[PDB]
Structure formats: structure tokens, C-alpha cells
RNA sequence: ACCUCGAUGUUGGAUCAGGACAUCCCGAUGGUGCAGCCGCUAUUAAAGGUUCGUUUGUUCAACGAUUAAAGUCCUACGUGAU
RNA sequence: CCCAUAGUAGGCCUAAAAGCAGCCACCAAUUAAGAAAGCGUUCAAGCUCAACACAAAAAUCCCAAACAUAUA
């Protein structure tokens, strides 16, 4: 992992999937070992971007997805 | 088609056929699955043998029993045939065998939530 | 064998039949019924008072922080007059309708951390949040006027 | 039903979802089975009923989603196991001895080498006890053990 | 699998089990005798 | 990592209670005790003082100190060197509510100790409970 | 480099108290076999063993079996050997039992109790039907201090 | 494995699974906890 | 003295005269110490049996070790071993009179409380070791609170009142319906079919 | 004290062994206070194997020397119309 | 399923035993939390309670054959 950006619009219809996602994985309890990552939360249907400096950009439209699905996708991508 | 018999329950694994060769250590116990793989006629033959009356006519009767593992039957036997008995068990249909009309005729039981992976 | 034995003595078959015949038969309760059709009040009064005490309100998701980092954040917020709160959605969802906050229902779900105040130091709070690139600000409602994040930014500036 | 599609970018799209047939015979019921009057009237071979609670790969669906009673969820799960072991769901598969009414997984039962005396015989289970309360159309009760 | 001693007499006997037929027979007799009680009560 | 110590300002080099416990992470005991003595000079001398040292991963010292301890402080205010045995019935010194308030005035000010409660009740009740756990009776 | 272990020598077996009878001699006399002696325990040196790290808990010497009928004696308990590094001092509570230095140097750390006597042991012209059944004497049990 | 008539989880990672007809307590962290019914 | 008192092996003054093995003292429901007295929890005897001094020691040690002396207190609800079981020699041909006393033991009937706990503590806090002791006991036993005891009793009356079986053991035995008194014991008229030997069938109405 | 007192002594040994597995060795596994070797423990496994001598009538036992091991048992304490 | 700020290592005796060798009180802050309910530390340190928040085995060789649903 190199960088991650979380964006969502609770001003519009809420999407708890990405909210739980950022509450869980975007926490220092994980970043302490995953120090290589840089998290940013730019909030304004949602969108979670993950930039890997090697060759990968991951874009998650976590509108109909849920926290477990997106967490598993993120873990699988990290494993690569 | 005695090769294609079906056992209810776990009889294929639990039913054990016991024989003795007569010699010491000659006790052989073989599950139904193993016996079926060895002889595709043995299971039906033994069932009939056990159901027949235990007298001297039993083996004469068993001479009138003709067991064939598959659809093939000798020509003379086929020419002898007179009637076909209805199968005792009606074979349940698979989904692959059900017609789309029948599927439609059967009602849907529940409303699945739209937001579900399935 | 004696009438009393260490093992359970075999009953006369007649006695066994008697027992079987006189075994208990439970009733059938008709069609299967299943298949058939003061901290709480302390929180109530405390939140009722808080909704009037506060003039500006905001909410965040301060769960991704550590114990020490949360303590430091609390210290920086107490430097000002603002106070940080948390309360169950289980009791807050009734509170929104109790205080007539219809637009606030789809804002509080999950971990929610209120930021009740009367004096906006939101400029410096946002500056502090900037060096920690997470924990985004969430919508609130100052004096019964719902503000989005852009509203809070404009109010700060 | 939402499905996840990949291209890397992955997204979830909600597709067409069936609805309960109109006019349930018994509206306002706990479970779908009770709503449709099927409490004791389905067996392992009723694939049309069973598949409605089955993941595409054969697994059962959770009780919260299905709405079934606890007892009816257990019955459906066991009937589905039996149907799978009988080969009645050839398409609901992850990717030769004919059986039916198989309670146990074939690979977990040991042969009955020593069936006991007549008064303590070791019997071979057939079907499931969960269906003991089904509708009885026969003069003698259907035997769960052979 | 043998029962020690002689069957049906000793401390250890063949387990005997009640069939539904036996239960029904006993219940039939009991019903007859309940009617006997009624007819002897007057 | 945070290291918590309750050392006495009077004796800056007791030995085992600092040496082995601090040497596991890798420390400069000379610098540590020099800074501790600097704080001892800054404050009254001869009193237990909690520390809030944080051994950074870069091998640097950032000592943080505040008010002295509370048990020893209350015992001294009550004129007690060693506390009571039972502490439920035993008592040796009596502290008045006015004295409790006067000492509490200079208690709710430290940052590390987190005793930053605005209300006076939060602190007075806490110190009263501490005294009650100790062998000190609260007069009036 | 220092260890305390507990040994427990085997307890002798208990004699039997039977009487023999056979078709033409109904009173065949005492028929109880003696019990077997308990198994000794022994410490032995090994150059392979470096230290007392691979030590264990109460080393229980095997107990001789009891006497049987037909005057069958009981097998004596098997000898249990414990192993220690070369140059191990073995002490009891102060008393030094042995300084085991040489390869294979071995010392008996706990004897096994003598087995009990069956009633036939007490047979004599005077005593024609003894019933006495001496139990197996216990074996020495002690704690050992091991230091290199 | 240790054979037990009653299976008891010992640590947090001890999990019960019914395999090949009988219950087992498996444990990744402490394989000493392995139990078989 | 909030601790369980030590029980002697045998009475100080023994019985010179040997007494017969009246198994009736184990057979049938218990009429004594069937109710709680200054306590909240206890060990209920779901069957009849004889409590040896070994059982007494097991109970005492386990309870004393696994209770809080200051809060939890215990009391014996059973007398000390007083019935001599004149077990004879370790081999001898039958006859020669009656044997001599070797052990002392106290009879217990079903429904009898054996040990009664009390003090400031709830039932689940005590269920564990009381259930272990109950299992250790020589007869069927159960860790029962006052609430659970009353609950199971009320359940028993519920069964007796709601059973749909027209035929009850009481009805048949008392009326001698099928001549079954030729097979029953005279004690069955009062045990109502719920007691067989020293065994008590709670499940049976 | 239930069968046998209207020609069956018994124990050991010899010969030949059939069987159980509650396994002594050989086989496959889990754990270990198993680094390796080693043991200890448990699951599974009965196809095969399971010594020779001194004293003693001895079964046993002790002792000597071995062995992969020198298993626990049942078979009318297997087997004397061998 | 979560995760556990801080008065303080509450004192007493205890080299120190701080929650844990033990007595006695068992208060307390934020919104919210038992000066100890279990591991593990000479003592500390590291982990979980919660609450925040959402049955079976014996010796010649197993022992009818089989069967789940056709009307009582
Ligand atoms: Mg017989
Ligand atoms: Mg007689
Ligand atoms: Mg003759
Ligand atoms: Mg085995
Ligand atoms: Mg014999
Ligand atoms: Zn229902
Ligand atoms: Zn574990």
C-alpha cells in the first residue's frame, strides 16, 4: 500500500459501507504496522481510491457494496 | 441396470456383507460400495436370495433370476420377455429435468432483499 | 433380587406396558405459536439539556484514534470552550424526532462524536485535522440551521 | 441481488430480483412456509421449493435473509443436504453410487461390521429425524432407521 | 452377543420392548374396563 | 513508549528501581537522573514525583513532570509518615474540608495527570475518596 | 546450572494369600506367590547431555507386581536410569551423594522396596495354612539437588 | 489430539468443528489444545 | 461459623445390636428436609442412595475449598453416617450368622436436600461446583436454587394437570384396572409410578 | 451347588496352534515440559513377528546372553483316544 | 462485536510486591467504567468479563433379507 483516498457524501443519501470502511481500516491500529500507507479523507456514489506506486490504481464504488466486501477486496489487492 | 441401483441412507457405506472362506482368518467383511464395485450384480442377487424362502427350492428359483448390470440384455432373453413390472420407486426429478413451465407454475416463496450478494 | 437394587431392575413386561401406556402426553398448543402472529432517563435529560445548551453542533468519527491521540485531541478541544460528546444512536434516533431534527436522521450512524460549542474555533480545529489526513468533518446543524461541510468551511472562513 | 463486476476497478450492480408470487394462501405468517401453507408438506425431493433458499453454488441462505422459522430453516437445510447427496441439484455445484435420503455425509460413516443382537441392533439411519412430523399418508410410520 | 444365564428370569435379561400393537391392546382393555366402572356405578 | 515511574526527588539514583527497568529499551541513566534532579531543584526537594517519560524510537528523552503524588501528600498534610494498616477503622491524622479544598486548588492543573475537570466537585470528591481509602477521616 | 528433581524408587509388590486345591488333593496348601521387588532408580552420566535443562519431574521407579496364585511370583520392577551431564554434583539436602564425572558413571539414587511375601513363604511343618500376606515394602523417595 | 468425552475450548482460538463424523477442538495458536471426541 | 461442619465416620457410641438392611429408607420420596431452611441454594437428591463417609469428605472438601467463607455459608441437611453396613470378611462361605460393622452410612431418599448454601451470592456463581459435587454424589443429584426448585415443582403440577393421556398410573393402579396390582408393589399406589426401586423418574407424570 | 460321580485326575513341559486387541516390535498419525537424536503421551493398525540358556516339576521368578520385540489374554487355567 | 482514558504504583506491612502474598476502604473525572473477575510478571510489563460505541472394546464367523410415506 502507498496511498488511499476516501470520499463520500453524507449530505446526500448516506452510505454506511464506506463510513465503516474508513472507521475500521483507516485507523492507526492498522497503520502502526502499515506505516507505508498515506490515508486521506476528502468528503463532499461514494469513491475509495488506492494508489500503488508500482502499477495499480484501485477504485471502489462502495455504494451497493458493504464493509466486509470492500475490506476483503482491499486485503486481496494488498496481498497481490 | 442392477449397476444403477440406489441405496437409501448411507447404506452404501454402512451395509456390510459378511462371508467366510472356511479357513482360519478367512472372515471377509465388505461394504456395499466395495461389493458393488467388485460385482455389479451381487447386491441385488443377495437381496433376492435373502428374501426367498430358505428351503431347497431357493436355488432352483435363483436359476430363474437373470441379473444384468447395464441396459444390455442377451437377445434370447429379450425375445423371452413378456411383461415389464413397474419400478417400485418413482425417481424424483432434478431441476435440470424440470420444465420452465413447471418452475413458473411453482410459486416464489419469499422476497429476497435486493441488496444481497447471493 | 431385592426390591431396591444398585442397578435398574428389569420390570415385568406388564409393568413396562403400563408405564408406556401411561406415559405423559403434552398438549398441542394449537397452530404453532411461533409460526403464528436510571441511566436511560439520565441520558434522556442530559441530551435534552445539551440540545439547548449548545449553539453550534458538529459531529466526527473519532474512533480511528489511539488512547493517547484521543487524549491530546480532547486537550486541544478543551483549550477552547468546545466539548466533545458521544451517545448511542440507540437513544439518539429518538432524540432527533424528540428535538424536531428530521434532516439529522441520515447523519448519525455508526460511531458519532458530537462537538458541541458556542464559540467557533473550527478554523483551528480544521487546521489540527489537516496534519492528520483522516477523520473528515461531518455535517451538523448550528442553531437549527443544518450546515454541510462546505457550510462549515464558509462559516469558518 | 447485487453482483460485483471487475475490469483494476470493481463495482457492485443490483440486478433483477424475483418477488414472492401474488396472493399467498395464508397472508400474515411468521415464515414463508407458514404463509404458503407448507409446514409439513415438503420433502427432500421437492427441489422447486428447496432451491428457492439456495445459493447458486449450493449453499444454504441465512435465516435472517430467508425469513424462515428456526425449525423450518433446519428442515430446509437438511432436505437440501439430502437432495444434493441424491444428485437432484446438478447445477448448484461448486464449479458413482446412487443414493437418496442420506442423512450423513458419505465419507464420515463407518461400516457396521458388528451389528448387535436383535435387542441392540445397530441400525442404518435413513432420512432425517427433522422431518418426523411431516404429513403421514401411510398406515405405518415411516422408519428413520433401517 | 449373548445374555448371561437363562433368558427372562435372571438379574440380566433380554431387553423387552413395547410395540405400538401392545400399547393399543392394553389401551383397548383399559377402555373396556372404564366402561365397566361406569356401568357398575349405578 | 511511555515509562511510568514514581521515584522520589530526594534520591535520584536508588538503583534497581531505575537501572534494569529503564535499560531494556536503551537509555542514558546519567542524562535521565540529571534531568530528574533539574526538576527536583525546580520543585521542592524530598517528595515522590510521578514521571511521564516517553522513550522515543529515535533514542531521545522527553521528561514530563507535574504535581507530586497524592497519597504521600495527604499523609504529610495529616502529619503521617506511614499510613494506617486497616485503613477502614484505623486513623492517625484528620484533615478538614477547608484543608482539602485548599490543597485541591493547586491540584486540578496538570496536563499529563489529566486532572483537568472544570467542576470543583469532580476533584474534591476524588480526593475525598482517596483519603477515605487511606487512613484519614474527613472532618465535617 | 542448578536443579532440584524428585525421585521415587519402586515399591515392592504385595504377596498373595491363596490356597491350592486340585482334584485328588483338596487341601493343597498355601498357594500365594511373593511380590516382586521394586525397581531401583539410578543416575548416570552422559557426555552428550550438556546441562540440567532437559530434566523432568518425579522420576518414578517402576513397582514390582503382586504375587499371584499357583505360587507365581511377581516380576520385579524394571530399573529406571536417569541421565545427567559429565561433572554433575548430586546432593541430597546437604549430604553429597556422588560427584559423577566419568562417562557412564552411575549411582543408585533410590532403592526399590523388597516385595511382599505370599502365604506360602510362611508354610512350614509348624504352620500348615498361613494366611499372612506381607505387603511390599516401600522404596526410598527423596529430592535431589543437581549442580554442575 | 487428546481424546475427551466432553470437549472444552481452552484459549480464544480453540474452535469446535465436526469432521469425519465426530467433534474436534482445533487450535492454530496452541496445537496442544487439539481435542477429539 | 460460615463453614461446613466436619462429619464423623461413625457415631461415638455404636449400635451393639446389628440391624437389618431396611432398603425402604432409600426407597420412595423423601418426607424430611424436603424444603429450604435458611439458604438459597442446595443439592437436591433426584434419587435414593447411601452417603458414605467418603462422600461426606468429598462434599465437605470441595464446598469448603470452593466457597467464600465470609459471604457464602453452608449447612448439612443430612445426619452423620449412622446406619452400619455390616460388610462381612474378604471371602468366606455363606452362613455363620450376620456380619460385623465395617462402614457407617446415612440413607438419603429422592427429594432430599443434602447440603444447603446461603449468603450474598447468586445462583450461577454457585452452580458450577454444586453441580460437580452433585455428579460426585452416589445418586442422581442436581444443583437447585429456591427458585429452580419451585419452578420444577410447578412444572410437575403443570404436567399432571395438562397431560392429554386419559390413562394415568394413579388411575390404573388405584382402580386395579387390568389386574396390574398383580404386577405392582403396594408402595406403587403411593409412589404413583414415579419411583422404581431407589430410582426416581422426574420426567414421568 | 445348576450339568457331569453307570472309567474323563491335576499342574507343568512337548507338538500343533485358532482367536481378541486392551499393541511388545514392525506401519501411519496428533501433542509434547519434541532444537536433532531421543524419549513421554494419545489415535489408528492384529498382515507379519514375538530368542536361547543356569537353578527349580514349576507355571511365574531371579540370573546370564540376546533381540526390532522377547506383549496382555481367551480357547474345558486350548491341546494326555497325540 | 467491540475495546478498554486518567486521580495513582490507594494505602498498610511488604527490598518493592502497584489488582494480583495478604487487610480495609472500595470513591472518582469526562459521556462513559469494579482501587480487582481470570492469564502472565520477584515486582512492572503484556492478554481475556464487560461497558463505551454498533463414549466406549474379547477372544471359531457379522448375523434373516430388506424397506423411510398407497388411504388407518
Ligand atoms: Mg443361556
Ligand atoms: Mg439349592
Ligand atoms: Mg456314560
Ligand atoms: Mg487399538
Ligand atoms: Mg477360567
Ligand atoms: Zn412459521
Ligand atoms: Zn487453543
Image (cartoon, coloured by chain):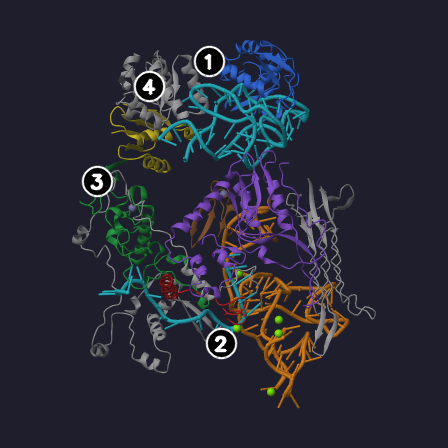
Chain colours: A yellow, D green, E red, F blue, H brown, I purple, J orange, K cyan
The secondary element bearing badge 2 is classed as: loop
Q: Chain of mark 4?
A: C
Residue H21: image x %, image y %?
42, 55
Query: What residue is disc 4 on?
Result: C58
Residue D67: image x %, image y %?
29, 43
- Residue I14's place in the image compared with J49, above or below, is above
User: Left or right: where does residue F106 sit relative to residue B86?
Assistant: right
Q: CA distance from mark 1 to mark 2?
A: 98 Å
Q: Nearer the viewer, mark 1 or mark 2?
A: 1
Disc 1 residue crowd, few under 14, some 14–19, many 20+, Cα 10 Å: few
- Residue F109's place in the image compared with G67, above or below, is above
Q: Are dots 4 and 3 on a single chain?
A: no
User: Left or right: where does residue F26 sit relative to residue B53?
Assistant: right
Q: CA distance from mark 4 to mark 3?
A: 38 Å
Query: What residue is disc 2 on?
Result: B23
Query: What residue is disc 3 on?
Result: D15
- Which quarter of the picture shows residue D123? bottom left
Residue F30 visible, this orientation:
yes
Residue D120: image x %, image y %?
45, 65
Q: Are dots 1 and 2 on a single chain?
A: no
Q: Chain of mark 1?
A: F
Amino acid at each position: 500500500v502507498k496511498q488511499v483516498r476516501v470520499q463520500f457524501c453524507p449530505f446526500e443519501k448516506n452510505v454506511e459501507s464506506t463510513r465503516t470502511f474508513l472507521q475500521t481500516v483507516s485507523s492507526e491500529k492498522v497503520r502502526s504496522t502499515n506505516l507505508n500507507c498515506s490515508v486521506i479523507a476528502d468528503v463532499r456514489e461514494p469513491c475509495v481510491d488506492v494508489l500503488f506506486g508500482d502499477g495499480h490504481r484501485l477504485i471502489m464504488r462502495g455504494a451497493h457494496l458493504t464493509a466486509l466486501e470492500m475490506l476483503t477486496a482491499f486485503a486481496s489487492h494488498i496481498r497481490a | 441396470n442392477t449397476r444403477h441401483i440406489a441405496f437409501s441412507g448411507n447404506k452404501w457405506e454402512q451395509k456390510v456383507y459378511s462371508s467366510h472362506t472356511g479357513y482360519p482368518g478367512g472372515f471377509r467383511q465388505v461394504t456395499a460400495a466395495q461389493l458393488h464395485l467388485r460385482d455389479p450384480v451381487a447386491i441385488v442377487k443377495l437381496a433376492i436370495y435373502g428374501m426367498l424362502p430358505k428351503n431347497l427350492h431357493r436355488r432352483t428359483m435363483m436359476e430363474r433370476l437373470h441379473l444384468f448390470p447395464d441396459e444390455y440384455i442377451p437377445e434370447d432373453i429379450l425375445k423371452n420377455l413378456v411383461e415389464e413390472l413397474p419400478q417400485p420407486r418413482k425417481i424424483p426429478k432434478r431441476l435440470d429435468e424440470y420444465t420452465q413451465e413447471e418452475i413458473d407454475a411453482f410459486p416464489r416463496l419469499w422476497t429476497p432483499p435486493e441488496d444481497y450478494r447471493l | 433380587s431385592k426390591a431396591v437394587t444398585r442397578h435398574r431392575r428389569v420390570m415385568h413386561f406388564q409393568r413396562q406396558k403400563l408405564m408406556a401406556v401411561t406415559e405423559y402426553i403434552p398438549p398441542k398448543p394449537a397452530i404453532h405459536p411461533s409460526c403464528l402472529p436510571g441511566l436511560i432517563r439520565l441520558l434522556r435529560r442530559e441530551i435534552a439539556a445539551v440540545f439547548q445548551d449548545n449553539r453550534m453542533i458538529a459531529v466526527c468519527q473519532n474512533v480511528a484514534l489511539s488512547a493517547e491521540d484521543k487524549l491530546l485531541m480532547r486537550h486541544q478541544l478543551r483549550k477552547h470552550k468546545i466539548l466533545m460528546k458521544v451517545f448511542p444512536n440507540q437513544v439518539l434516533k429518538p432524540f432527533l424526532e424528540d428535538s424536531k431534527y428530521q434532516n439529522l436522521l441520515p447523519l448519525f450512524v455508526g460511531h458519532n462524536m458530537l462537538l458541541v460549542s458556542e464559540e467557533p474555533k473550527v478554523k483551528e480545529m480544521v487546521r489540527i485535522l489537516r496534519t492528520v489526513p483522516f477523520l473528515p468533518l461531518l455535517g451538523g446543524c448550528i442553531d437549527d440551521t443544518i450546515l454541510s461541510r462546505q457550510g462549515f468551511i464558509n462559516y469558518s472562513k | 441481488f447485487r453482483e460485483v463486476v471487475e475490469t483494476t476497478i470493481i463495482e457492485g450492480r443490483i440486478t433483477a430480483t424475483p418477488k414472492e408470487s401474488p396472493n399467498p394462501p395464508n397472508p400474515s405468517g411468521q415464515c414463508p412456509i407458514c404463509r404458503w401453507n407448507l409446514k409439513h408438506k415438503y420433502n427432500y425431493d421437492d427441489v422447486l421449493l428447496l432451491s428457492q433458499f439456495i445459493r447458486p453454488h449450493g449453499g444454504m441462505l441465512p435465516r435472517k435473509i430467508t425469513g424462515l422459522c428456526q425449525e423450518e430453516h433446519r428442515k430446509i437445510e437438511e432436505c437440501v443436504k439430502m437432495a444434493h447427496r441424491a444428485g437432484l441439484l446438478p447445477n448448484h455445484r461448486p464449479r458413482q453410487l446412487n443414493r437418496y435420503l442420506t442423512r450423513w455425509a458419505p465419507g464420515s460413516v463407518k461400516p457396521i461390521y458388528k451389528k448387535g443382537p436383535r435387542w441392540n441392533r445397530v441400525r442404518m439411519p435413513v432420512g432425517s429425524p427433522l422431518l418426523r412430523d411431516n404429513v403421514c399418508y401411510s398406515r405405518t410410520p415411516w422408519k428413520l432407521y433401517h | 452377543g449373548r445374555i448371561p444365564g437363562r433368558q427372562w428370569i435372571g438379574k440380566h435379561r433380554r431387553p423387552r420392548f413395547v410395540s405400538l400393537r401392545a400399547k393399543q391392546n392394553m389401551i383397548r382393555r383399559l377402555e373396556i374396563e372404564a366402561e365397566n366402572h361406569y356401568w357398575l356405578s349405578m | 513508549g511511555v515509562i511510568r515511574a514514581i521515584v522520589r526527588a530526594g534520591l535520584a539514583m536508588p538503583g534497581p528501581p531505575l537501572g534494569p527497568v529503564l535499560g531494556q529499551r536503551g537509555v542514558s541513566i546519567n542524562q535521565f537522573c540529571k534531568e530528574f534532579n533539574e526538576r527536583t531543584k525546580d520543585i521542592k526537594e524530598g517528595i515522590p514525583l510521578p514521571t511521564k517519560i516517553l522513550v522515543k524510537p529515535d533514542r531521545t528523552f522527553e521528561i514530563k513532570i507535574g504535581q507530586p503524588t497524592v497519597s504521600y501528600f495527604l499523609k504529610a498534610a495529616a502529619g503521617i509518615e506511614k499510613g494506617a494498616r486497616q485503613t477502614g477503622k484505623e486513623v492517625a491524622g484528620l484533615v478538614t474540608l477547608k484543608h482539602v479544598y485548599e490543597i485541591a486548588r493547586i491540584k486540578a492543573q496538570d496536563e499529563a495527570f489529566a486532572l483537568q475537570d472544570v467542576p470543583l466537585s469532580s476533584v474534591v470528591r476524588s480526593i475525598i475518596g482517596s483519603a477515605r481509602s487511606l487512613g484519614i477521616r474527613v472532618v465535617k | 546450572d542448578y536443579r532440584r528433581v524428585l525421585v521415587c524408587g519402586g515399591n515392592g509388590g504385595a504377596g498373595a494369600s491363596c490356597f491350592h486345591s486340585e482334584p485328588r488333593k483338596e487341601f493343597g496348601g498355601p498357594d500365594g506367590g511373593d511380590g516382586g521387588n521394586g525397581g531401583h532408580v539410578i543416575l548416570r552420566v552422559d557426555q552428550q547431555v550438556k546441562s540440567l535443562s532437559s530434566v523432568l519431574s518425579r522420576y518414578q521407579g517402576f513397582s514390582g507386581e503382586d504375587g499371584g496364585s499357583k505360587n507365581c511370583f511377581g516380576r520385579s520392577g524394571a530399573v529406571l536410569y536417569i541421565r545427567v551431564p559429565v561433572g554433575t554434583l548430586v546432593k541430597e539436602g546437604g549430604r553429597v551423594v556422588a560427584d559423577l564425572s566419568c562417562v557412564g558413571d552411575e549411582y543408585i539414587a533410590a532403592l526399590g522396596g523388597a516385595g511382599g511375601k505370599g502365604n506360602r513363604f510362611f508354610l512350614a511343618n509348624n504352620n500348615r495354612a498361613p494366611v499372612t500376606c506381607t505387603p511390599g515394602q516401600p522404596g526410598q523417595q527423596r529430592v535431589l539437588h543437581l549442580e554442575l | 489430539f487428546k481424546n475427551k468425552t466432553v470437549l472444552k475450548k481452552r484459549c480464544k482460538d480453540c474452535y469446535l468443528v465436526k469432521r469425519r463424523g465426530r467433534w474436534y477442538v482445533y487450535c492454530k495458536t496452541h496445537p496442544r489444545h487439539k481435542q477429539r471426541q | 461459623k460460615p463453614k461446613l461442619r466436619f462429619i464423623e465416620r461413625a457415631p461415638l457410641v455404636p449400635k451393639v445390636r446389628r440391624e437389618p438392611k431396611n432398603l425402604s429408607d432409600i426407597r420412595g420420596p423423601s418426607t424430611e428436609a424436603t424444603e429450604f431452611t435458611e439458604g438459597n441454594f442446595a443439592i437436591l437428591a433426584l434419587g435414593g442412595g447411601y452417603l458414605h463417609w467418603g462422600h461426606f469428605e468429598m462434599m465437605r472438601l470441595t464446598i469448603n475449598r470452593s466457597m467464600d467463607p465470609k459471604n457464602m455459608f453452608a449447612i448439612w441437611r443430612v445426619p452423620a453416617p449412622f446406619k452400619p453396613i455390616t460388610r462381612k470378611s474378604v471371602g468366606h462361605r455363606m452362613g455363620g450368622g450376620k456380619g460385623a460393622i465395617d462402614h457407617y452410612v446415612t440413607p438419603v431418599k429422592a427429594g432430599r436436600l443434602v447440603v444447603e448454601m446461603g449468603g450474598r451470592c447468586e445462583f450461577e456463581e454457585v452452580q458450577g461446583f454444586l453441580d460437580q459435587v452433585a455428579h460426585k454424589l452416589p445418586f442422581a443429584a442436581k444443583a437447585v436454587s429456591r427458585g429452580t426448585l419451585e419452578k420444577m415443582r410447578k412444572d410437575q403440577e403443570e404436567r399432571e394437570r395438562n397431560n392429554q393421556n386419559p390413562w394415568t398410573f394413579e388411575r390404573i393402579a388405584t382402580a386395579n384396572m387390568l389386574g396390574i396390582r398383580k404386577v405392582l408393589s403396594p408402595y406403587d399406589l403411593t409412589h404413583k409410578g414415579k419411583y422404581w426401586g431407589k430410582f426416581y423418574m422426574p420426567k414421568r407424570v
